Amino acid sequence: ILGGREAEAHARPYMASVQLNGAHLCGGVLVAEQWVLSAAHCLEDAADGKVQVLLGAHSLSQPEPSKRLYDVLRAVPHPDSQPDTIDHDLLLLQLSEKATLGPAVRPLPWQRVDRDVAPGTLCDVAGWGIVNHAGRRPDSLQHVLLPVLDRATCNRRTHHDGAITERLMCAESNRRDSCKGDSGGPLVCGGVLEGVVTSGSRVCGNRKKPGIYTRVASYAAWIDSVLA
Ligand SMILES: NC(=O)c1nn(CC(=O)N2CCS[C@H]2C(=O)Nc2cccc(Br)n2)c2ncccc12
């Protein structure tokens, strides 16, 4: 998270850290007792390595009572997801067992009505992604409040030149933005999950290249299908 603040410990109990060989890769969001929603291309180049989902965390390294690790029993990517496109950038991870729920571990209600978040709405994006262009990896959870950007502006040739479909959404990226590692992380508006940070490589912190987030409501039927 570029231009953010360290988040209040365990204030976002839905926050998950998708890790490979005990190293953070992507953010994730607890949507059910045994399901974590993330971005499609997070497990890319993972291959030979231990994939695990860290729950109840604030510091990635320090001991915390709430901190628990889960094996991934099943990894369900969206059927139409491909590394060449930023489209259908969703991944549903089934944990080995149901999450031990508590004040620091709680699933987030996600948007089940396909209606765009009104431009200018302030949304909260959190994660353990890089905090500066050099690439500083933060130990503790960071977060930033960003206003939702009008798709028309976002699709300008100077911006994402039409790449932003009706299934995607934008947020402002003027210094304060999401970045490498924030992928698969949640975009929350009015305490409801609205978007999922894309896992597609992009330029961060430049205002003319807005942050891209997958609209969960746009994939509500698929998510329901998998979870059931
Ligand atoms: N949404 C983004 O801004 C974004 N996502 N990605 C993809 C992305 O972050 N990922 C997809 C493969 S696993 C994950 C990734 O590269 N994670 C990572 C790498 C180094 C440090 C940290 Br903390 N996290 C970007 N890559 C480069 C620049 C920006 C991004």
Image (cartoon, rainbow, N blue to C red):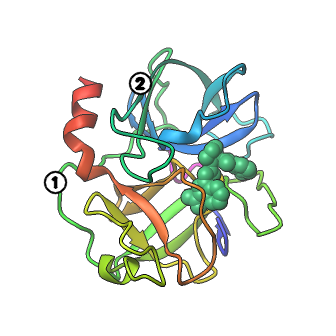
The percent coordinates of residue 22 (x first, y second) are: 76, 30
Q: Residue at x 70, y 30 (%)?
A: 20
Q: Which mark is residue 1?
A: none
Of the 4 image quadrants, the one containing the C terminus is top left
Q: Is residue 178 above or below residue 228?
A: below
Label 2: state its secondary structure: loop
Reading the image, the residue beneath label 2 is 34
Q: Main secondary structure of the magenta part?
A: loop
Could one spot residue 127 in this view of the protein?
no
In primary-sequence order, the first of circles 1 and 2 is 2
Of the 4 image quadrants, the one containing the N terminus is bottom right
On screen, residue 163 versus residue 133, left or right, reads left
Extent of the magenta region: 9-13
On screen, residue 212 versus residue 62, left or right, reads left
The percent coordinates of residue 141 (x first, y second) are: 66, 54
Q: Amino acid at mark 1?
A: Val
Magenta stretch holds residue 161: no
The percent coordinates of residue 105 (x first, y second) are: 50, 37
On screen, residue 180 versus residue 208, left or right, reads right
Q: Is residue 209 above or below residue 101?
A: below
Q: Residue at x 34, y 77 (%)?
A: 121
Reading the image, the residue beneath label 1 is 113
Dot in front, 1 or 2: 1
Foreground of the two, 222 or 72: 222
Q: Amino acid at mark 2?
A: Gln
The percent coordinates of residue 76 (x first, y second) are: 40, 26
Q: Is residue 68 above or below residue 141?
A: above
